[PDB]
Image: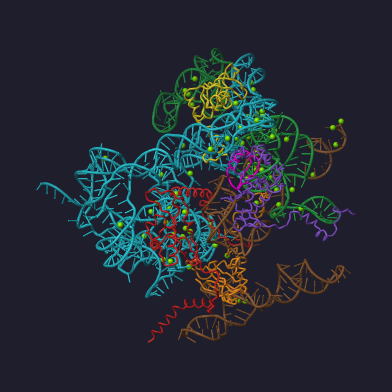
Chain colours: A yellow, B orange, C purple, D red, E cyan, F brown, G green
RNA sequence: UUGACCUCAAAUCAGGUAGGAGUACCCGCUGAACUUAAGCAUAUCAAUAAGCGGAGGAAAAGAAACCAACCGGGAUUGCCUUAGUAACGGCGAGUGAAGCGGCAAAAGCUCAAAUUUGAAAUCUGGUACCUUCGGUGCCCGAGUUGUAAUUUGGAGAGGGCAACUUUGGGGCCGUUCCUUGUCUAUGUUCCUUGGAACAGGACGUCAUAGAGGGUGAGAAUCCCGUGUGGCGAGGAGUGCGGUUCUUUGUAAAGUGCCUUCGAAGAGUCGAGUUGUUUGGGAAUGCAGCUCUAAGUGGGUGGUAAAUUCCAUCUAAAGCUAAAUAUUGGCGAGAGACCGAUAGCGAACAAGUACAGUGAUGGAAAGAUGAAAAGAACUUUGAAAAGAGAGUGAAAAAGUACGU
RNA sequence: UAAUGGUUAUAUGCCGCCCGUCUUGAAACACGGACCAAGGAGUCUAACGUCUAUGCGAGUGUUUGGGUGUAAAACCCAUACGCGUAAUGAAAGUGAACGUAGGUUGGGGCCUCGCAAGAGGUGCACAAUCGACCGAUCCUGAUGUCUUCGGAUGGAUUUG
RNA sequence: AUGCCCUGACGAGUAGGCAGGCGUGGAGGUCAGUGACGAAGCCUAGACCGUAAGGUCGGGUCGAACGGCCUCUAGUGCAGAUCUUGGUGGUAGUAGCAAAUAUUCAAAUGAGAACUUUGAAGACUGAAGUGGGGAAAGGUUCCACGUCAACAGCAGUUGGA
């Protein structure tokens, strides 16, 4: 249970802090777990998700479908992965919103800041 | 507990226990003590005789710590000696080592004679005593000592 | 300024606590109040003082299952239900059952090790909450005593030889010498004094 | 209205009393914050014991004069008889009250001993030196409690001299009652011729 | 002629400062009526609402012109009690304290003045220079119609003689706290239902973490958090280890005897009267007016006066933290509260839309779906739309959308 | 088995005025109601009275505070304070056993004798009655005293 | 064992009293309660229990929670208050849309013309005007294009919409 006197177990307070979270705070909310390979390879379990990361859907109707994320659509609290789209009846292709907690990251888009974030969380980076 | 009241039993019946003819109003007798000398006098006399009028002297600036004189009777008087040591004073009832009871330290101002201490001599340090209370202590072989 | 907090006499508070500790003895009320304690060897369930220094929750639930509180533990966390009204959005979202109360004398880790376990509550012998001992005003909480806790209960409440360690307190007297009247009624000294009985359902004459 | 056989009540509720209802919901909250303050203060006023040494005084007002209690401060004569100055006494935690005076030698000697016992039991650190720490005790009251003095021994011989001790009360009431009237008749005996 | 002094001016002179807001709580002033008294004028409501002036994080009060009458206590504030009492009152309705006692918190002090008279030793400003919440030098000024040192009634001051003891200040990092960053467990394994598994069944794992929230249905183990610890970053008049000023130094301060003194607040205390107020009763406080003080004496001692004592303080000058209040602001955490006719008037572009010349008044109004996947296309019709077709788990969810 | 029976609609015979309300009296040509949904009216508090339950009981009341805590909970505690153990009087004051804590009449239960009836003893609570004790009231006024204080004693359907 | 049973008598009722129960919101306990294989709600001249308050079940609709029992608690039960807020009827396709002399023919546009546009005709205000401007007030109503769901109490392709 909660022991501190600054964190809150109020439901109304906690849902307001979720649904009105700004973009930089929705980045850590929209985290995604890593695969069996990557957790073995780096030593970290989940990462705040980025655009050109490669994911595998492990839940829902699109389960088992691979792809690369085209957009982290933080206003809708969702990601849109390429190649996981919906055909409209008028030939169009709208993307399907996925929540990143139902994804699994299979390849990291790495730069210096992702590398620094892995070593900050105590990761191997190998 | 709101469920145990008769408001819950008066749901459905029109007058809520107050009557139709009477027809419960704001204040039919006047508020508070209205008309105690006029239309409540048969209740003011009969259950409260003596309410109206003055009685004797006014005391300006009365301090009740002047009048502090709590009374202890000789029907107790021995409870002030603790219960363990009390039995060895009642037996071996003697002068020349008699129990000392600081009446004031127990918080009494006057000693009164309600009755029948044993025949054990005691030394009583009272602020005040009565006449009979003085006599009964001395008839048991004790003494009354005055302290302030 | 409606009256919220209610006053009870301190002795009538202690009267109820003593009668609640007495109800955590023999198992009829402990079964009646829930508390799966059929396969317990004996009640009161006293375990060693070594429980008071368990500091890991893994080692704490190993000890409670080993002394037979496993079915009481699994009675909680299979009774987690959503609350049945408007209170689930007044921070009272989930309901579950009460588990075994663990009573100690020294905290050396047992409170924190049993903190996360659903349903298992802890208590010092010096406190012994009535809201824990008779939850729902229902006598007979399943209590696991430590050995130091069980010895200290003579000091905290008194005996016929040791006073109470509370000022002026004595454990309450009985107004009847036994709870069984059928033994008294069937005693030889009463059964001789009585006349012979009737048919226990009368024959309808006329 | 006036109704059945019931006591006459004196409820004072015909002002706007509902504006001035104070319900102490914060009794438990103020207790934690008072206990937080004492812990905060004791850390701030480390090793010093959180309160001053107060004198023993005799309570006033004949209802209460059978008791002693803690007073306000140690009565400049008492500080001087204890062997220190009032200004230095105020810096090692002795309360000094300038406005009380001594007329009881027994209360005086009880307070000088109380001041001498205090100086024996306190360690006073150097004003700038090394000063190794010496275990804060949070109360001067519990270390130096106000003990009531014994009034008599528990057992004595009976000394009844026949004075009757209720006549004593009746006579001493009557010398006060007629004190002025028999000095006036005495001086009006002495102003004849 | 000239040079001051005093009083009064002026300047877009040099530097400052006041206004207004908010106002829950706080200090004042001003001030009702409805109401009750079964009518009503005293009274009560009420020393209230309304009106006005002034502050702060608290304010006010506060180190006795006190309470008492005891063996006496000892600044103020607040709680429990006193006590619905003493007392006031058409002695009617009603009103109504205080001392003691137990606690919470504690804290004490400063001027008026002594002739420095062998130092106006004191201070603002300008200017210069530094180590700049200031310091040093110089100059003008203020000021003897009194700025410093010394003293504040508990005392204390001058002089004389045995005395001994204590000498202060500034940076630094770590150490207190405020903020804030970051890191810190364990399944998304299998079967069934399902559109969706977060459901059920099986087998585990973590737990100082099974608070909470999110994610397509009830998720400790998917995610964020939570729990416990770590590592930082920036700030706080600093409790503590070194520091440095080191002829900071016969400076200053405590304390013992003798001796001479001991200044202590005026249209003020007090009195009468008027009005108001009080529980305050031959008068509780306040204010107007009139009269107007004393120096081993002035107040108080709850029945007016005279006489005799006694007791206790030392007014007419001033500062002061904490306990205490807080329907306002800022930040939190809660609830046996309410659940869209409820709860704030307002869950929503709400004090909004709108009404009024204006002061003011003042709403209604939440919910498709897990995702717009918000109905391509065909056909009928001028079109709205229909009928098909589709999407969707469901169109008995089609933006007129949960039930 | 819808055969009996249930429900329901209808038909037939007989009965049946519109509810609520105030009123002596309502179907009234007395008042309110066109209809429906939702809301909608003896509450909380301070101080108490009777009764009842519970704890302790000549005492009782921890919760103003303090300690403690898993933190508005629970648990623990000193000194007070309130109420009660003493009344009476306007007040100064004074202040409760002649006695087996009284006598008489009843009185349950108990004890003894009794087959039972009854008899006798003891009789709590309670009821009536006559007393005694404390205060106040009105009388009496002892020994003593620096002679005006003191108040012993004995009094009453007077009083509380 | 406020159980089981035997026996006897009784049963009107306003105001009113009391007792035993039914139901609602929330709380403590419990039923390791029910539940997306369908909770709650709602409809049901289908069923069952209870004298009754009510309770239970089946069917249909529906889609996320909710019950029994022992207790706690209250913002707890509606037919009335010319109650409050909202919704809806009958009256009823009724009353009415009758002041200001008045319209008519053809063509055009259009899905659609009593009402629009043009032409023709008839008329009127009749210069103290139904004419040209302005003040106050309004505020974009002016003008063009597009448009006709609502508004112009008929209509509308027209319009100060
Ligand atoms: Mg009735
Ligand atoms: Mg009525
Ligand atoms: Mg009359
Ligand atoms: Mg519900
Ligand atoms: Mg006194
Ligand atoms: Mg004195
Ligand atoms: Mg004294
Ligand atoms: Mg200027
Ligand atoms: Mg104020
Ligand atoms: Mg004020
Ligand atoms: Mg009144
Ligand atoms: Mg009136
Ligand atoms: Mg009147
Ligand atoms: Mg009138
Ligand atoms: Mg007034
Ligand atoms: Mg005001
Ligand atoms: Mg401010
Ligand atoms: Mg403060
Ligand atoms: Mg101040
Ligand atoms: Mg002073
Ligand atoms: Mg004081
Ligand atoms: Mg009282
Ligand atoms: Mg008043
Ligand atoms: Mg007053
Ligand atoms: Mg304190
Ligand atoms: Mg000096
Ligand atoms: Mg599962
Ligand atoms: Mg969910
Ligand atoms: Mg966790
Ligand atoms: Mg959760
Ligand atoms: Mg740790
Ligand atoms: Mg003065
Ligand atoms: Mg005034
Ligand atoms: Mg007045
Ligand atoms: Mg001040
Ligand atoms: Mg506020
Ligand atoms: Mg609704
Ligand atoms: Mg609303
Ligand atoms: Mg307007
Ligand atoms: Mg809706
Ligand atoms: Mg979805
Ligand atoms: Mg269609
Ligand atoms: Mg559906
Ligand atoms: Mg459709
Ligand atoms: Mg539907
Ligand atoms: Mg639907
Ligand atoms: Mg058949
Ligand atoms: Mg059949
Ligand atoms: Mg039939
Ligand atoms: Mg008929
Ligand atoms: Mg009638
Ligand atoms: Mg009628
Ligand atoms: Mg009707
Ligand atoms: Mg009508
Ligand atoms: Mg109506
Ligand atoms: Mg309703
Ligand atoms: Mg008598
Ligand atoms: Mg008498
Ligand atoms: Mg009947
Ligand atoms: Mg019933
Ligand atoms: Mg309920
Ligand atoms: Mg289930
Ligand atoms: Mg259903
Ligand atoms: Mg129907
Ligand atoms: Mg749904
Ligand atoms: Mg209601
Ligand atoms: Mg009804
Ligand atoms: Mg209705
Ligand atoms: Mg009705
Ligand atoms: Mg209406
Ligand atoms: Mg209509
Ligand atoms: Mg018509
Ligand atoms: Mg016509
Ligand atoms: Mg004409
Ligand atoms: Mg013409
Ligand atoms: Mg146009
Ligand atoms: Mg039209
Ligand atoms: Mg039209
Ligand atoms: Mg136009």
Which residue occupies the foreground of this view, E313 or G66?
Answer: E313
Residue range highlighted in magenta: C94-123
> Is D180 situated above or below E187?
below
Percent position of residue A87, x then y: 59, 18
Answer whether residue C1 is visible to the viewer in this image: yes
In reply to whether residue C99 is colored magenta, the answer given is yes
| Residue B92, picture quadrant | bottom right
Which residue occupies the foreground of this view, F137 or D156?
Answer: D156
Q: Could you tell whether D148 is left or right of E162 in the image?
A: right
In reply to whether residue D150 is colored magenta, the answer given is no
| Residue E264, picture quadrant | bottom left
| Residue E380, picture quadrant | top right
Which residue occupies the foreground of this view, A120 or A92?
Answer: A120
Percent position of residue E345, x then y: 53, 40
Which residue occupies the foreground of this view, G36 or E25?
Answer: G36
Q: Could you tell whether B144 is left or right of G40 in the image?
A: left
> Is E132 situated above or below D3?
above
The quadrant of the rendering that contains the N terminus of chain A is top right
Percent position of residue C59, x then y: 62, 38
Give the residue at the far right of this rendering.
C206
Answer whether residue D16 is visible to the viewer in this image: no
> Is B55 situated above or below E203?
below
Percent position of residue C160, x then y: 66, 57
């Amino acid at each position: 249970a909660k022991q501190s006197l600054d964190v809150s177990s109020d439901r109304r307070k906690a849902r307001k802090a979720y649904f009105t979270a700004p973009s930089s705070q929705r980045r850590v909310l929209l985290s995604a777990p890593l695969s069996k390979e990557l957790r073995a390879q780096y030593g970290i379990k989940a990462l705040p998700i980025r655009r050109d990361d490669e994911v595998l859907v492990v839940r829902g109707s699109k389960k088992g479908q691979e792809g690369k994320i085209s957009s982290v659509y933080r206003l809708k609290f969702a990601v849109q992965v390429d190649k996981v789209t919906k055909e409209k009846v008028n030939g169009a292709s709208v993307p399907i919103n996925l929540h990143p907690s139902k994804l699994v990251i299979t390849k990291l888009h790495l730069d210096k800041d992702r590398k620094a974030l892995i070593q900050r969380k105590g990761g191997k980076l190998e | 507990p709101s469920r145990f009241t008769k408001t819950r039993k008066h749901r459905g019946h029109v007058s809520a226990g107050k009557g139709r003819i009477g027809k419960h109003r704001k204040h039919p007798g006047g508020r508070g003590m209205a008309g105690g000398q006029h239309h409540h006098r048969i209740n003011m006399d009969k259950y409260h005789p003596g309410y109206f009028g003055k009685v004797g002297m006014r005391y300006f600036h009365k301090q009740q710590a002047h009048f502090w004189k709590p009374v202890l009777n000789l029907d107790k008087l021995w409870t002030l000696i603790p219960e363990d040591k009390r039995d060895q004073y009642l037996k071996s009832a003697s002068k020349e080592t008699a129990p000392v009871i600081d009446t004031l330290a127990a918080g009494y101002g006057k000693i009164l004679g309600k009755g029948r201490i044993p025949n054990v001599p005691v030394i009583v340090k009272a602020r005040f005593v009565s006449k009979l209370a003085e006599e009964k202590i001395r008839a048991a072989g004790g003494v009354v000592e005055l302290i302030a | 300024w409606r009256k919220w907090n209610v006053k009870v006499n301190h002795n009538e508070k202690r009267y109820a606590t003593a009668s609640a500790i007495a109800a955590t003895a023999v198992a009829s009320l402990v079964l009646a109040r829930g508390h799966r304690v059929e396969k317990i060897p004996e009640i009161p369930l006293v375990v060693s003082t070594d429980l008071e220094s368990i500091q890991k929750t893994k080692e704490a639930v190993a000890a409670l299952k080993a002394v037979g509180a496993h079915s009481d533990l699994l009675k909680v966390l299979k009774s987690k239900k959503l609350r049945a009204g408007k209170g689930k959005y007044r921070n009272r979202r989930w309901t579950q059952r009460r588990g075994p109360l663990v009573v100690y004398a020294e905290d050396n880790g047992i409170v924190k090790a049993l903190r996360n376990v659903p349903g298992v509550e802890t208590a010092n012998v010096a406190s012994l909450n009535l809201l824990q001992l008779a939850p729902g005003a229902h006598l007979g909480r399943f209590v696991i005593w430590t050995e130091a806790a069980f010895t200290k209960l003579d000091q905290v409440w008194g005996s016929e030889t040791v006073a109470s360690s509370k000022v002026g307190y004595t454990l309450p007297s009985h107004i009847i010498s036994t709870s069984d009247v059928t033994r008294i009624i069937n005693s030889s000294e009463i059964q001789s004094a009585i006349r012979p009985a009737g048919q226990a359902t009368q024959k309808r004459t006329h | 209205a006036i109704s059945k056989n019931l006591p006459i009540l004196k409820n004072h509720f015909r002002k706007h009393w509902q504006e001035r209802v104070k319900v102490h919901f914060d009794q438990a909250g103020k207790k934690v914050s008072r206990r937080n303050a004492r812990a905060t203060r004791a850390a701030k006023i480390a090793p010093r014991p959180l309160d001053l040494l107060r004198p023993v005084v005799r309570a006033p007002t004949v209802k209460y004069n059978r008791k002693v209690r803690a007073g306000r401060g140690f009565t400049l004569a008492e500080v001087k008889a204890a062997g220190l100055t009032a200004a230095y006494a105020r810096t090692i935690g002795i309360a000094v009250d300038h406005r009380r005076q001594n007329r009881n030698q027994e209360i005086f000697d009880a307070n000088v001993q109380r001041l001498k016992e205090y100086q024996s039991k306190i360690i006073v650190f150097p004003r700038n030196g090394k000063a190794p720490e010496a275990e804060q005790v949070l109360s001067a009251a519990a270390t130096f409690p106000i003990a009531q003095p014994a009034t008599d021994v528990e057992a004595r011989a009976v000394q009844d001299n026949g004075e009757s001790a209720f006549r004593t009360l009746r006579l001493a009431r009557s010398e006060k009652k007629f004190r002025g009237i028999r000095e006036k008749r005495a001086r009006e005996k002495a102003e004849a011729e």
